[PDB]
Image 1 (tube, rainbow over the protein chains, first blue to last red):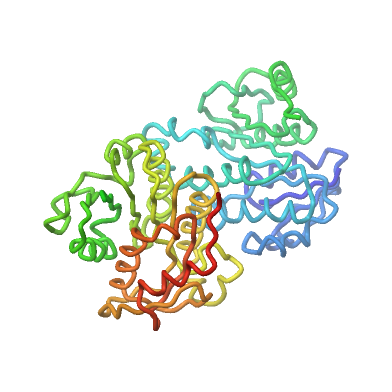
Image 2: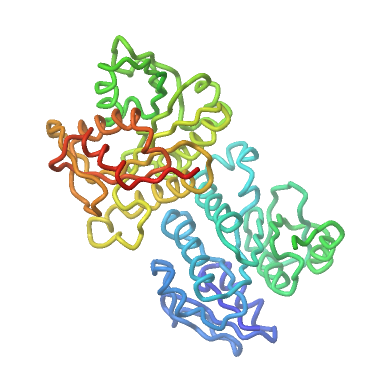
Length: 219
Length: 219
């Protein structure tokens, strides 16, 4: 399918482009500076700016089959990028009539009651920004969404092994986060779902398959 | 009635306490440091912290007839105070079963399409924080709310004269903002309404009265 990536030139974005480069998808990598997009045979760089309005953004999203948001500001522009930019992209997706939307968020983003201790204290502003964007996606859109909520991101080599939905905050390699997102594209039962993850013991495909047991589709 | 104030020790809060000091209301002035609350015969200082959870906040709100939020961070803690703190207070009001809620926001807070030019550019982060809190109040609560949206705040002497709902961004004295909020407490037809203001030509009471002409109550 045709997949549009926002956050293409960030660390997770670059890993995701690498991950998607070996698929049959046509990838459209949004970037403020198109020349900064890493080159792959199935990747086309598209001018895209998080500071744009939803209508400006929507111009680039026509005919896409899915949109993946892996855009962050490294904590340096939380209101503009991680919150407002993310929400404007959701508004843009709806304007462009693109239903499938995958958002990279963070462990416990919708559970402020679990923002406990010095680790969450240090990331409080980040948590607030991500929280409100996730509320918007889950409450104020009609998108076929999936929110993936990893723990701390590491640059260690991908293990291929994760565990999910266990209320655990633990680290995960960026490569495994990217590969999980890649698999979520092909996981229709994850539509309307919020999924937490960390590095663990279960192959990514099998881990996501294990969600079929108790997921219910809302007619 | 019994009115709880959040933001009591800030500049607008102190003006609002002065304004309310000459009413028949019983004022409960929330503050992190109770000793910082200016003293008035009808004002009781109550320990209140924006960093608290909704449930912690709700403990202080029992038996209040109205809650007024005039809390800001002077642009220094927008995610924690102007957005998250404001939203937690709304959640607290509902938990405490207090219906009447008046929020100080800002001109065009719900109209991003009017955030035009260098003035709005400089206040973009503030605008984003206020925008999302206003969306929450208007879309994700069942409160009997009023949002007042003044233009730039000045410390000039109150004129008693304003104009409202004219799509104009212009300055207003803090005293006139405080006195408008005071009048809104007694203006039941402003429930469920968003009202913009600046200094102008119309006495505050008369200006608010002029809203009866076309306001509709949603049964």
